[PDB]
Length: 25
Length: 24
Length: 24
Length: 25
Image (cartoon, rainbow over all chains, first blue to last red; front, top):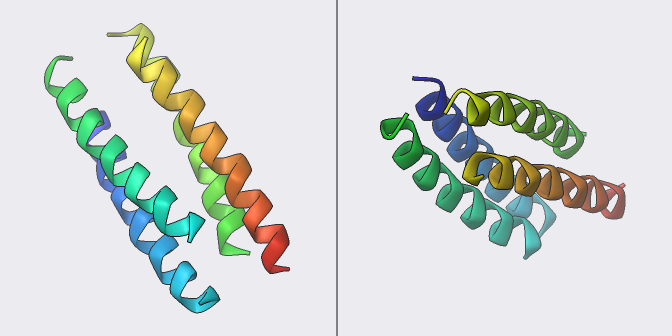
């Protein structure tokens, strides 16, 4: 449970970092 | 640039944590 | 702003993973 | 071992995100 939830959270963070990278372009 | 590399690393880490979760 | 909030979250996650590592 | 190494890596990532946040200021 916990490690799968953390894994999903890291993917959510990764998606947001790509959004910020684009905003930064 | 670096933010997209960090994002790719975090996706790779997510994959590894799912594997560890099953072990556990 | 958001990058510093994400950094704080990642430090919190790091703390939790250390706890899980001991369990396992 | 592995989860402690990942934890250290997430702290390393967090430090770099703060560096990028500052560069963005």
